[PDB]
Amino acid sequence: GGLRSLGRKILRAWKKYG
Image (cartoon, rainbow, N blue to C red; front, top):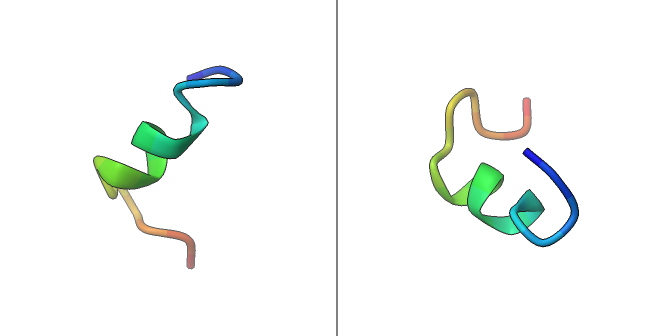
């Protein structure tokens, strides 16, 4: 997880925000 991947970090929705 990094700068440009930040979006795909959300995209994978591991825990999804909250």
